[PDB]
Image 1 (spheres, chains in turn red, brown):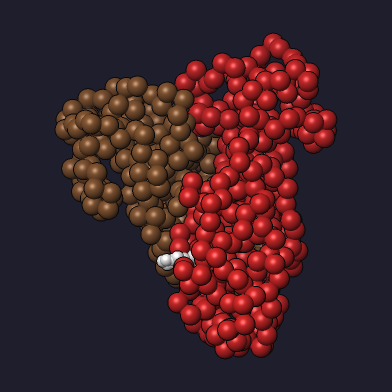
Image 2 (cartoon, helix red, strand yellow):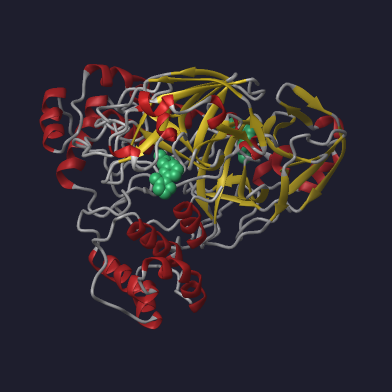
Length: 304
Length: 304
Ligand SMILES: *CC(=O)Nc1cccc(N2CCCC2=O)c1
Ligand SMILES: *CC(=O)Nc1cccc(N2CCCC2=O)c1
């Protein structure tokens, strides 16, 4: 029993983290096969970040200017190219610890683990969600850029995130491993504000299932609702519209608990309208939206 | 910026996890040097657990009855002994991935990372605290026993916890790596209830410092208090008495923020008396008590 905000084991990703230095900028790179991936802003001074022309800035950089260090051993850079907002540094040595991997571009509402690194060294691991506004709520200091987000399916790491920047509101923006930003964000130090942080309705419902499975049941009520009725209440509280797709995704948790998805929607409706009344659900005083239905099934069944 | 419930990177511990089978019971073992550590209840049937005599049960077990598997390779057991509530299985092969390690017995209020495993395979990593009632609030299914809790100081893993049992109230009890239970708990399936889950005052104050450092400041007020005055309010709300030792431990965070510990105590007092009023602090709707002052400094400074 018990339900915890749970990251993937970080070992496979720890083995891929390197230090990248260009001039006075040190951040992290991801070493897979003979390629090190890092944010292209490694080449920028903080002054550059105001209005950088990356193609022009990059012309002044040679292979020997990219200092790549795996623990205490230097890697030889034999090539470099810019792909969107990442640099791919070709090194002469394949990472012997390269796990099976994919690059995946995730959807908002999807969760992933971040291995926070500084100077190519792991500091910690925490679970995130791609927010509906395409930000993440991370923990990232200067030097943490190039830290990656990932999922693991058995032995295959799916990298979905590289950390690039902090918005003045303390939320985080980054790219997939092809270097495309999630959402409208740019690697420039400019006026970028996040849109509405809407709550991931399908994840809250998943987490309400996890609560019932783990003994927290006080919020179950005698009511049901319809998608359309629920969605009126969703709109009012800046929750994502619930779709039949979301209902279908919750089917296994419905089946396991014997609570119809729409009945759980009616519970969530009363919770939105009436609050917690100073009660908690799985040790939380608000509705948690960074567990996917897949996360709930994984944790509740003990997948490794 | 940003502050997250953050586990240690699990790689060093992943390298130590093995499967232990005795008869029909499979759980996890910790392989350090040529010793595998696992809960002594590996030798019990669920029927045994009602009133087990471990010395007597153990007499019927030989080295060849302890099936120890690291990934897909079997380890030869050349010795076995019981130390308190753990078994030490001597194997003929030193774990080549043994990190630098210590066994430490932690105090209540101290935090640690758990690597949840099933069948010697990592499922996930989350941060815990030894509760003042000597329980932890974990995520543990059948097969997760022998999962360990740890801290890392640079390159040295300090193992503090092995998971042994779930109380009927869904909270968790276990041992240090010498096999001594935290608190009054026994590896018997019996009437064991947890005492009062008191809140770790010093950790809440640490976390209020982390909030101020990361921009969440609405709860700062014009008031101060005394240890004795604060402790009246602590008593009422089942918070640990705040000691001068706790005040001294918060000194660095006080210095960094310029908020006197007793002024932060006065903030915490108003929060206890008046609630959050539907506001959040570092994305939480309750007062978080599973960050130590050390955790806050580590995360806020980017220690690796
Ligand atoms: C994105 C990131 O991590 N930025 C970064 C890397 C290295 C150094 C910095 N600094 C140091 C102080 C000024 C600054 O931006 C930032
Ligand atoms: C402590 C722990 O993990 N217990 C454990 C290990 C292996 C198998 C079990 N089971 C399976 C179903 C009944 C039972 O107790 C428990």
